[PDB]
Image (tube, grey):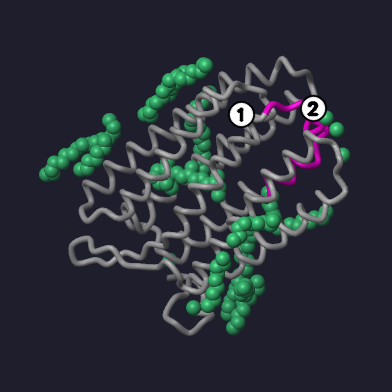
Amino acid sequence: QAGYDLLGDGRPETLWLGIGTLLMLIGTFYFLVRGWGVTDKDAREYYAVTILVPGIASAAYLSMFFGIGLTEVTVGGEMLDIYYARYADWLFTTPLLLLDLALLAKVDRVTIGTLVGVDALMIVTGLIGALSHTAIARYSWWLFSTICMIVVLYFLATSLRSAAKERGPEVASTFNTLTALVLVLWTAYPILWIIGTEGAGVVGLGIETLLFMVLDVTAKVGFGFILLRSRAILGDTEAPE
Ligand SMILES: *C\C=C(C)/C=C/C=C(C)/C=C/C1=C(C)CCCC1(C)C
Ligand SMILES: CCCCCCCCCCCCCCCC
Ligand SMILES: CCCCCCCCCCCCCCCC
Ligand SMILES: CCCCCCCCCCCCCCCC
Ligand SMILES: CCCCCCCCCCCCCCCC
Ligand SMILES: CCCCCCCCCCCCCCCC
Ligand SMILES: CCCCCCCCC
Ligand SMILES: CCCCCCCCC
Ligand SMILES: CCCCCCCCC
Ligand SMILES: [Ca+2]
Ligand SMILES: [Cl-]
Ligand SMILES: [Cl-]
Ligand SMILES: [Cl-]
Ligand code: NA
């Protein structure tokens, strides 16, 4: 794999995992310190949700860097590396990012349940695909997971967008800018997976780990930076509970 075997354990992708860990930690601490000076009850909710996004990713990246949760999946003559913490991270952080968007939109708890349930199914079926032992199974689960992603993104772009519009320009503009980021960046994930080690195998583990690290940092720290600097986070919220 393209990279550098930092820990001397035969894993050049640790260069990227290590850089990812550092960036996630810096982002977590930045949001934490910025949050300490926030008093508005709504803004504090966005900070709490958002700090946890690079925070949990920090833990996952540190895990992966040290090789905790790494195994091999047999696919014919090949043995493909799977990091469980990648999927566990996404399982927690994608619902948190969706909750940020749902708070902005001020949508009801059944809408939120639908959005996060389909998102959880997306991640679970991606994991099943990653653990599957035939190409046909891996591609099939990938397709199912991708359909789930399209459903999530469609809900964001329609139902939540229309709800956010009613909340006036500040909220609408922030919702729209973050949704623009999400529709593009999230779609990059299935593309990378299917061209990479889990799918067609064009892109190797090194380049793939690098690019997932860039996507992760952008979709977590980048997203959070954009959200938390906005006046929209001062607007009234209604948590699902
Ligand atoms: C770290 C934060 C984010 C935004 C992660 C997003 C992850 C996905 C959108 C993953 C999607 C997948 C699909 C649609 C198909 C199977 C392969 C994936 C699990 C990578
Ligand atoms: C104004 C001070 C900024 C401090 C932010 C620290 C976070 C560093 C992590 C890098 C995140 C890059 C996101 C990419 C955006 C497209
Ligand atoms: C209170 C109004 C919101 C109603 C939302 C529920 C709609 C049902 C959609 C179910 C989506 C599951 C599809 C699974 C992914 C292929
Ligand atoms: C010789 C291979 C054995 C038979 C396997 C065929 C499975 C094909 C199913 C494809 C599932 C697509 C998921 C998308 C949701 C409709
Ligand atoms: C209103 C449309 C909602 C559904 C959109 C789902 C797919 C998003 C399309 C964006 C494609 C980005 C490609 C980037 C290639 C690097
Ligand atoms: C001998 C070891 C060579 C190390 C070369 C590292 C290349 C540059 C590191 C930056 C990686 C991209 C960061 C993306 C930020 C989100
Ligand atoms: C032999 C040690 C290589 C360290 C790579 C660091 C690259 C800068 C981010
Ligand atoms: C309050 C800082 C972020 C906490 C992240 C939780 C996961 C770490 C194990
Ligand atoms: C919750 C953080 C996971 C990383 C553990 C580090 C163990 C080093 C051997
Ligand atoms: Ca307020
Ligand atoms: Cl405040
Ligand atoms: Cl207040
Ligand atoms: Cl590679
Ligand atoms: Na290493």
Residue type, numbered disc 2: Gly
Where 233 falls versus 80 (above or below)? Answer: above
Residue type, numbered disc 1: Pro
Where 94 falls versus 11 (above or below)? Answer: above
Task: Determine which residue is flagged by label 1.
Answer: 240
Q: Percent position (x, y) of residue 45?
A: 73, 39
Question: Taking the image as drawn, is residue 59 in sight?
Answer: yes
Residue stretch rendered in magenta on the structure: 221-238
Picture quadrant of residue 180: top right
Q: Percent position (x, y) of residue 86?
A: 47, 57
148 relative to 4 in the view: left or right: left
Residue sitting farthest toward the left: 76
Task: Determine which residue is flagged by label 2.
Answer: 235
Q: Percent position (x, y) of residue 110?
A: 52, 22
Q: Earlier in the sequence, mark 1 or mark 2?
A: 2
Which label number is shown at residue 177? none
Residue drawn at 49 percent across, 30 percent down: 152
Residue drawn at 38 percent across, 55 percent down: 196
Picture quadrant of residue 94: top right
Quarter in which the N terminus is drawn: bottom left
Q: Name the main secondary structure of what is drawn in magenta.
A: helix
Q: Is residue 234 magenta?
A: yes
